[PDB]
C-alpha cells in the first residue's frame, strides 16, 4: 500500500522459502548463496523440506551471544541447486530501535501476509518460552501462531525474524551484518 510494504514485498518475493521441520511450517529468510535463517525452536535436523522439496542440511548453527545466551537464530546452509539474492547490505550493523516496521509471512496457512507493526523497541532480555534470550525487538501487535520466521523490515533494512509473542506484543530476534560475514 506504501513504501514500507514495497520494500517488504521485494524481500518476500526473492528471499523467502517455506521451510518445514517436524515442528511445523516456517517463513525462512535466505540471506546469500545457500545460507538462510529460521527460529532455533524449529529444531532443524539433517533433512528439511524447502517449498515441499526434500533438502539435505549442509550445516546448521544455533547462535548464542558471547555471554553464552540464546539468540533464537539458527543459520542453515541448504544443499539447494540455486543461490539467494545477496541481501547482506540491508542488514544493520548495530542493535537499534526503529520506526514503522512491517512483519511479512508466507506459509500454506498465511500466504502473502503483511502486518504494519509500528514502532520497534530494542527490548533486550526476554524469557522466551522459559529460555533466557538476548537481542530481542518488541512491537505492539497481537501476533499469532503461524507467524514465526516472519521477516521484520523497515524501508531499506531487514532487521529481524519473528520468534514469539504474549498475545499483546510480538518479539523478533535481531539480524546483524556480523552474523553472515564469510
Image: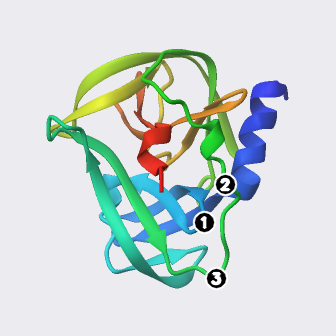
Query: Marks 1 and 2, how far apart in space?
Result: 7 Å
Query: Is 106 positioned to the left or the right of 27 in the image?
Result: right
How far apart marks 3 and 2 lie (CA) works out to: 16 Å
Whether the residues at callouts 3 and 2 have beta carbons within 8 Å, the answer is no
- For marks 3 and 2, give the one nearer the viewer: 2
Look at 49% across and 15% down and name the residue there: 97
For disc 3, the marked residue is 81
The vertical placement of 27 against 2, above or below, is: below
How far apart in space, not on screen, are marks 3 and 1 (Cα)?
A: 10 Å
Q: In the image, which disc is placed on residue 33?
A: 1
Disc 2 target residue: 86
The answer, for residue 144, to whether it is visible in the render is no
Image location (x, y in percent) of residue 71: 29, 41
Whether residue 33 is visible: yes
Which SS class for mark 3?
loop
Residue 34 appears at what percent x and percent y? 56, 69
Amino acid at each position: 500500500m506504501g513504501p514500507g510494504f514495497d520494500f517488504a514485498q521485494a524481500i518476500m518475493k526473492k528471499n523467502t522459502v517455506i521451510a518445514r521441520t517436524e515442528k511445523g511450517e516456517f517463513t525462512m529468510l535466505g540471506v546469500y548463496d545457500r545460507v538462510a535463517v529460521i527460529p532455533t525452536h524449529a529444531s532443524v535436523g539433517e533433512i528439511i523440506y524447502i517449498n515441499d522439496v526434500e533438502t539435505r542440511v549442509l550445516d546448521a548453527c544455533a547462535l548464542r551471544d558471547l555471554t553464552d545466551t540464546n539468540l533464537e537464530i539458527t543459520i542453515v546452509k541448504l544443499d539447494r541447486n540455486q543461490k539467494f539474492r545477496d541481501i547482506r547490505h540491508f542488514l544493520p550493523r548495530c542493535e537499534d530501535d526503529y520506526n514503522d516496521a512491517v512483519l511479512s509471512v508466507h506459509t500454506s496457512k498465511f500466504p502473502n501476509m503483511y502486518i504494519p507493526v509500528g514502532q520497534v523497541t530494542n527490548y533486550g532480555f526476554l524469557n522466551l518460552g522459559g529460555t533466557p534470550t538476548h537481542r530481542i525487538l518488541m512491537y505492539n501487535f497481537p501476533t499469532r501462531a503461524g507467524q514465526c520466521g516472519g521477516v521484520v523490515t523497515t524501508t531499506g533494512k531487514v532487521i529481524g525474524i519473528h520468534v514469539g509473542g504474549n498475545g499483546a506484543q510480538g518479539f523478533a530476534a535481531m539480524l546483524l551484518h556480523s552474523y553472515f560475514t564469510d
